[PDB]
Amino acid sequence: ATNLRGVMAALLTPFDQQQALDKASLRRLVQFNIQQGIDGLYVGGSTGEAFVQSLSEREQVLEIVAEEAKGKIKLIAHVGCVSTAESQQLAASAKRYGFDAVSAVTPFYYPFSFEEHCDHYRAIIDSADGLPMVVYNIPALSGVKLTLDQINTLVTLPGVGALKQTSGDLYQMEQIRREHPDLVLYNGYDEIFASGLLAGADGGIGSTYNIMGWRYQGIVKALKEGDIQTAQKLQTECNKVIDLLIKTGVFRGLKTVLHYMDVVSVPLCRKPFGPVDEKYLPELKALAQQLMQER
Amino acid sequence: ATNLRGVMAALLTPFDQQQALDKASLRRLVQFNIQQGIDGLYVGGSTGEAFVQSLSEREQVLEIVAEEAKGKIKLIAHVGCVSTAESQQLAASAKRYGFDAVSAVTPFYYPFSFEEHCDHYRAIIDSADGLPMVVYNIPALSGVKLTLDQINTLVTLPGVGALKQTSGDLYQMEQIRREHPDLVLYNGYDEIFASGLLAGADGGIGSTYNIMGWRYQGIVKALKEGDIQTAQKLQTECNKVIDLLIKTGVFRGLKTVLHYMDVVSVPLCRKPFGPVDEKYLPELKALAQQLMQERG
Amino acid sequence: HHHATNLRGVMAALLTPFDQQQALDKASLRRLVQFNIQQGIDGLYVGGSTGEAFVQSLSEREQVLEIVAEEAKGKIKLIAHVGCVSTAESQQLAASAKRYGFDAVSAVTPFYYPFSFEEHCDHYRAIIDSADGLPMVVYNIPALSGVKLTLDQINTLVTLPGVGALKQTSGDLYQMEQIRREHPDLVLYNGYDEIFASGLLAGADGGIGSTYNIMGWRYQGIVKALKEGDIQTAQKLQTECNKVIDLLIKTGVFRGLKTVLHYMDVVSVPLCRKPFGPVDEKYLPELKALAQQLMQERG
Amino acid sequence: HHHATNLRGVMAALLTPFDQQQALDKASLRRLVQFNIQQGIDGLYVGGSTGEAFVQSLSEREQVLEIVAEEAKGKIKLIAHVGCVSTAESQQLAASAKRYGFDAVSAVTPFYYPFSFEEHCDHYRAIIDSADGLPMVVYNIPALSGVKLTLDQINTLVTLPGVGALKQTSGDLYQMEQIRREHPDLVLYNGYDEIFASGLLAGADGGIGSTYNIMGWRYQGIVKALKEGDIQTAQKLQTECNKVIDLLIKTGVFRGLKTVLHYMDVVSVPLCRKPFGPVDEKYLPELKALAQQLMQERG
Ligand SMILES: [Cl-]
Ligand SMILES: [Cl-]
Ligand SMILES: [Cl-]
Ligand SMILES: [Cl-]
């Protein structure tokens, strides 16, 4: 799955004032990401507010993104739901729309065993019908640090093409790379991107790529050139942003920056997310202006 | 909300081998719980496998349980989703079908503030159109211990009529009762029911009540009569069963017991839940036979 | 386990009074032992966490053990908490407990460094050997130790030869019941004072607690009320205990207790050792009012 | 922070050799000090967790401090970990560190009892006063201590008067970067050896680690490779360190390290103190083979 290697934005879902999909802003956001030189888009993930959308709504996003982006950048459909059948429906739809890959978060909420996770992934792969699968290692959600044997099991499942390493454990990052030298291994926490690459990730998937994807592409290139100072500098700038976004609320802060970038019409998330606290708007607008100047 | 007090079974949702809703087994389960002398049913909760069902399916179940049980026992609809809008849709449906109350788990997965949980409950309460609301204190999911002040804010939200205390912290159970003398306070962990009552809970909502609700009613009665020994003995028997169900998988183990009690046609949970390991079937069948004899 | 039957009951986890220079206040320590004997406490648990053992040297701990033995041997049951991280240090305290005439030893699961479960077992075996006949109380406090024993592991620990009891300092009352179910004759001490009534109901047959220093009689009252089937009295007593515990959590538990004991004319100077700070002066009125209230309910 | 810049670098967290009877092996201690110096290490961190401080008496820890200072003062930097639960005990060790001529002191956040943040700050202030001019290395540590500091709390700790450095025993490299961003001149030691390269990239300017005892030159290699922009050499070296760390985690880290040193003819007897058990015999060939491989990397 070498063709899945790279820096992929986890696409946000713009909503209108009534919390319905803002189709026009979705299309603007897809093109905005393409123009940033991003390798691909990760669509319908946690970042896309998948877990406050219906299946129909998730499919509509997939279809529109494919319309805008197919044959220009890589497209990975996050089809994960708690339910295997629901996840399967989305995988089949991803295949129809011509996505390059599917992905599923570890089924959550209820206590599922590792065996049940594996069967879940097998069924989704079947429904994906030739599309490779990106599986997760996400301890914050699962409540489990899986062993290296379990990871081997996961990443050697027939059809699995990559691992989204959504963990800040860079010893485990290095251990996974050592065990699987050819594995596509996405760094999941944007705020350790540079260090995650050094530890052995060969790319990433992240929410903040939407507004500053060129910075992350800059880190990749700097590290390839042995330019440690440039890499560090860029990560420091990314982290200044992540500091602010955690204060504001990450998705809504991102949408607001995009609103000031003239991409997103209405920067709301779906309830129960509240609006951005108005005291942060000047910082978010200033950030949008700073980012716009970096282009 | 005092009429919401008591022992409420968290109803399981029967499915068939296609993973479709088994409507005949659902009606049978509802009647079986009524015949156990249960005070009510808590429908479409986590226990009811809500989070692997669509809104429509949850509505179908709510409507059918209301058909079978409205007027005979108390009915609480769990309408909780991550999405407020979705929760409001189910709240409005619960009202239409004639439920006595609604309930919603803390919105999960994403990081939401306590203020955002409160606005979420307010929106659901509005859509429930006069039905009282049961809120949760569920640290295992929320990943936080709520201050007494936060609980105090929660239970005094307008329209909130009970707290589902899904915590094994019996110091906090007492603190809550001490602060809110008239609060309807449901013990959430079946395996500490007797001790939870002793600490201040005045009832419970439980998945295991589906197969042995009379034992939990028996603990209420024994504690009211000052019969500590019978209370302890019954809790011990419930915990022998809980030990087994934790090994088998709780929901599928319960459905399997009900299958052996001739209530549920097919004891499956929805994928990604797998089947019960067949080595446990003799124990589960033997347990069904023991429970049937207790009635007898 | 049946041979350990005489260890069943309500045991105060003794505090260690210090003077203004943070040295042992022997006169106050002797006072506190006698105060606890006069409350009709079944026994004393000496040199535990409550005693500030982990800010004491070995010699200081032996000194406390020897003094308490001088005051109380033969009058009430005495359990010596001998636990340190080091097994050799623990053994030295265990031998001393035997020399001074203690009825039992106890050890917290060795902490800080991750030790294997087999290493915990050998630690307990070594201490049991040095205790030379005195039975062992296994002391379980996941919240402070950071040691997370499984039920299987607990079952193995409590059946080690020479083990006569379990100090269960856990709020998990499902586990409490599971332990009782597996070991019908085991002496099973409830460790969190704020759930005492519920813990007894779940299957503890007594408790070891720091708050017993100032209101042991309330906890004995709960044991009696449950045994008689008087659930109302049991609940009411537990509620009063929890009102006190609410205050103590605000003030800091050890120092709040010593302050109450100061106002009861037991403890001269209610200091804990650094880095414990002093009680906030705004809480003194509440602490004095509690001392007065508690002195009243004895008649 | 700028005036304690000379503590920047790669500092081995010194192990404490014990003899067959588990008493201090002074001879082997002197030999381990010289072994570390000959590796080109910048300094030693003495009497930390790694040095088995928490299974030693105060006198034993002082004896170790005196011996190391004898062997190494003036040749490399020396940091005395003086941390105990007790402030007065930490102050004794701090006064001794000053007497033996150490360059800095350090103290783990006091553990077991749940101290407030203000209490932690006063504990450090008191130790800083007793160290009488030696700068303090503070801790940010949860996995071992159990103490869970916020970033704002870390920022207050590291700016206390007399604090010259932070030992960041955390795998959180976002926080590592945040700390560097807030404090440009702070000496910031990477605490987890297994992420050393990544930790330097995030902002650490050196480290303190147990595995430096057997392969310190590899970590100095990483520093140098990263300074020269040779990312592949850095990754390669970190990968080799991690293969060793994988084995040490299987064997038990301190005892595994001691066994490697025994095979390198640095340490006479590779025992840790009870309740640490011995290395399982089945790992000995791997440990001997590791010793030979490391001896070859410099011979
Ligand atoms: Cl995502
Ligand atoms: Cl439920
Ligand atoms: Cl104690
Ligand atoms: Cl150390």
Image (spheres, coloured by chain):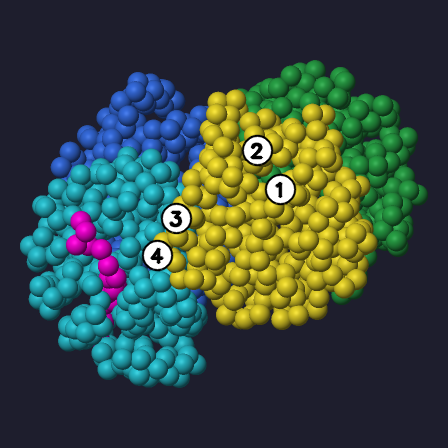
Chain colours: A cyan, B blue, C green, D yellow
> Could you say whether the residue bearing mark 2 is in a helix, strand or loop?
loop
What amino acid does circle 2 point to? Met
What amino acid does circle 4 point to? Leu
What residue is pinned by disc 2? D264
Q: Is residue A4 visible?
A: yes
Cα distance between the residues tagged 3 and 4: 14 Å
For the point 48% across and 25% down, the residue is D285
Q: Quadrant of residue B295?
A: top left
Magenta stretch containing residue D166, yes or no? no
Per the rendered image, the range of residues in magenta is A1-16
Cα distance between the residues tagged 4 and 1: 34 Å
Front-lying residue, B250 or D83: D83
Q: Is residue B180 left or right of residue B108?
A: right
Question: Looking at the image, do the residues carrying marks 1 and 2 touch, with CB atoms under 8 Å apart?
Answer: yes
Question: Residue A197 got which mark?
Answer: 4
- Residue C201: percent from left, percent from top: 58, 33
Earlier in the chain: of badge 3 and badge 2, it is: 3
What residue is pinned by disc 3? D236
